[PDB]
Amino acid sequence: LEDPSGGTPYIGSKISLISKAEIRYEGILYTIDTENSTVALAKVRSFGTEDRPTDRPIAPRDETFEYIIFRGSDIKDLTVCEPPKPIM
Image (cartoon, rainbow, N blue to C red; front, top):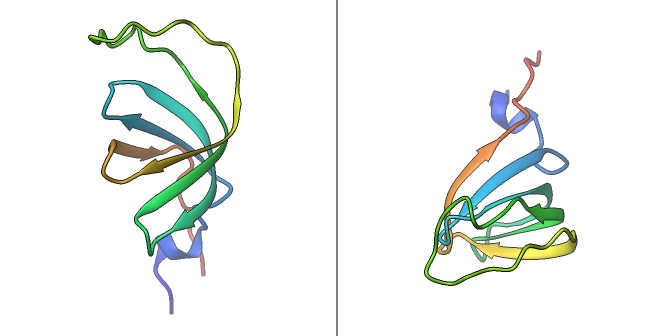
């Protein structure tokens, strides 16, 4: 007996994360560290900052980062794109 959400692994799925700076980052779930309330995403890129006006000007960048770490404290919201499929 197992829960439906548990049946589907979060790692390997596409996720979108919104940070405290009102910037939207997209990447793939690489590793989850529950013990330290931290998540590591690989192959991640930032869509833009101008979409959410801030007091700190940010220059445009079209480069992708291999590895970036975010902590639950700084993160504002987390949404998954791939939903879990029925299991039996």
